[PDB]
View 1 (cartoon, helix red, strand yellow):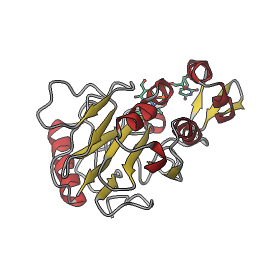
View 2: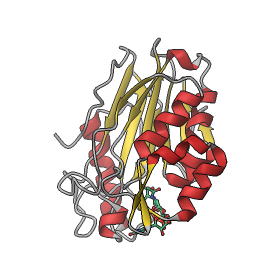
View 3: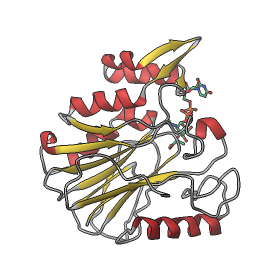
Length: 242
Ligand SMILES: CC(=O)N[C@H]1[C@@H](OP(=O)(O)OP(=O)(O)OC[C@H]2O[C@@H](n3ccc(=O)[nH]c3=O)[C@H](O)[C@@H]2O)O[C@H](CO)[C@@H](O)[C@@H]1O[C@H](C)C(=O)O
């Protein structure tokens, strides 16, 4: 349909979905289910696309949209309204509360515990992934990392994610083993954002990791991609306790 449903061993109390570009009202280059409000689209179309996602996903409440800044801060969803939503991840243990991250190449990661009593969503672009957003998201859970599941959503894969030293140096400063995930490609590198996520998740003891098969740049019928399109829309990934 419009929506991707993560293929992971989802506990009964957990629901998740990840949007695609299909099924909205936005015009090119935002065509069509653009959920992002700061990328130059018509605000009335973004509002309608967000309502369509709400209906298609059977969400129990409106998603808690974050003021994403490519950092490592996590908002605990203790109840609307919020003083500040300046964060790149959210955490919930409240039934019906919808965690949401907005992406167009950055890695969305969805998290839940085996008990299906706590969920989280993280926006892991290269800058936030390097800074520790995933480790910070795991640290918000009451449960131990051995009992946490992670789903790697659609991101820019290593076929397409060309980077320079701004990026490789940053990662090698935090954890030298990141070098494996950078492959020389002329004067630049191809970076494997899924590998870097798997490193950071293993570092905090998250072992049960799913997804990581999609490519936002390559699969242009399905996804917006900042790197491919420059001016483009945003998908989002969603998780909640039923
Ligand atoms: C995957 C990811 O983190 N993408 C993010 C990143 O874009 P990116 O595309 O990486 O741009 P760069 O940071 O400016 O550059 C990162 C590195 O990549 C080199 N490069 C860039 C372009 C190119 O063609 N070739 C090339 O080698 C460049 O020299 C630098 O070393 O930075 C943008 C903000 O500037 C974000 O909006 C974007 O977030 C997305 C939307 C989201 O939230 O989903």
